[PDB]
Amino acid sequence: GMEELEQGLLMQPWAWLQLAENSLLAKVFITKQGYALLVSDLQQVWHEQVDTSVVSQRAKELNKRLTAPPAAFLCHLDNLLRPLLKDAAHPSEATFSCDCVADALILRVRSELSGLPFYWNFHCMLASPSLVSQHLIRPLMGMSLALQCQVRELATLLHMKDLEIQDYQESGATLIRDRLKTEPFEENSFLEQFMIEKLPEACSIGDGKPFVMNLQDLYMAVTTQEVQVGQ
Amino acid sequence: SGMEELEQGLLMQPWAWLQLAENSLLAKVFITKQGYALLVSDLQQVWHEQVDTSVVSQRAKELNKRLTAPPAAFLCHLDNLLRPLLKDAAHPSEATFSCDCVADALILRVRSELSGLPFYWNFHCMLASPSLVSQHLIRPLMGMSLALQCQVRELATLLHMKDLEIQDYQELIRDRLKTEPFEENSFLEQFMIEKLPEACSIGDGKPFVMNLQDLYMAVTTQEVQ
Image 1: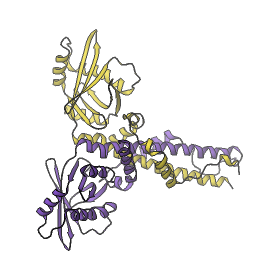
Image 2: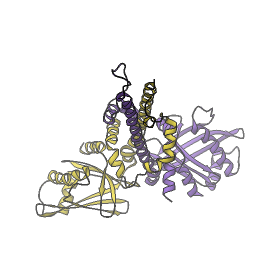
Image 3: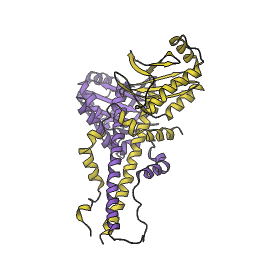
C-alpha cells in the first residue's frame, strides 16, 4: 500500500498553496490506505507518508468533537486538497498554516466535517535526495530537453515557411518591397535577442505559481514516462 | 571570504560530462589560488566538496611526498588537468580518472604525472546540502523550462505571422511546395504523442550538457541578483 502511494504521488502535478504567511508548492496522493505528500518552498523539499493507523491515531489527537473511520478522514482530506489544487479561485472555507522545527515542517489545516470543526496536521520531514531527484531534478531536466526539442521543431517549421515565401518571391509575386514583412528566421539572432530582451522576465520563478500554471501537463507527461521506463 | 567567492564562481559554471572507466558523472568545478568548490551528480544524488589552501597543502603533501611547490601551483595543475577536459571530452587527457563510493561519500580520484614524477589528487565529496541542490539544479532547471516555454510561444507567434503573409501571396504556385498552416494545439498534441518519450530521456546527462548549458548559465547568472 505504501509503494502505491509513492507511485501515485510521482504522477501528481504540483499545486500552489496559499498559507497564512507564505505559500508552498504541494502534491499529494490519497487513497483508503493513507497519503503521500510532497511540499516545497523552492529552497527545501519536505515529505510525509502515512498509513491508516497513523490517520486513526492523529485524528483522535486533533479531534475531540467527532470520530469516523480512517478512510472517511482520508476521503475528506482529498475533497479539501483536490479543488484548491486546480485553482485557488475556489470558495474554500478551509485554512492552512505552517511552522518549522529543524528539519521538520508542520502543515496545519482547519476545515469543517459533519458541520463540526475538523483539524489535521501534516508532519513533514526533509525529503530524501532520491525523492528530490525523482520528483524535481530528473523531470525538470527531462522537461527542459523536451522544450528544447519543441524549439528545434518550430525552427524547422519556420525555415519551411520562409522557403515557401522565397518560392513566391522568385516567381514574380512581388518585385519591389512595398511593406514591412517578417525577416527570414535566423535562429542565432532569435536566441541572442531573446537572452537580452526576454530572458530576465521569462525565467522568473517567483512564488512558483508560473510553474504550476504553465508547465504541469508537461511535468505529468515527463514523470509518467520515467515510471514506465523504470519498470 | 575565500569560500563565498568560490561558491559564487561555481554557480556561474556550466555542467560538464565526465567519462570514467566504470561510469560517468555530471561535474562542475571552480578553481582559484584560494582553493576550489566542486559539485558532482549521477542524476540520483548530488555531492559537494570545497577545499581551502590548508586542506590543499595537507592533502597534496600526503599524496605526493616528493613534491615541493605551494598550494597555488598545485591548484594550478589541477585546473590544467581538469578544465580543458570539462570543455571537451574529445580532448587528449594527461590524466586518468576513477570514482569510488564509500558510505554516503563520493571520492573522485586523479592519476597524472608532473615533471617525471607521479601526480595524485583525491576530491572527497559529501552529500550536497538541500540549498546547493536547489541553487545549482532545481531553481535553474525550473527557470529554463519557463524560459524555453516562452521561446516556443514566440516561435508559434512568428509561424502564424508568416502564415498570414503566405495566405496574402495567394492573391497560385505548385501545390506540393505549400506548407500546412501552423496550429499550436495540434502541434503540441502531436509532439506529446509522437516525440515526448524520446525528447525527454536524459540518459547519462550528456544531452543536457551538450544542448542546454548556454541557457543554464544565462539562468544562474540571472538569479544571483
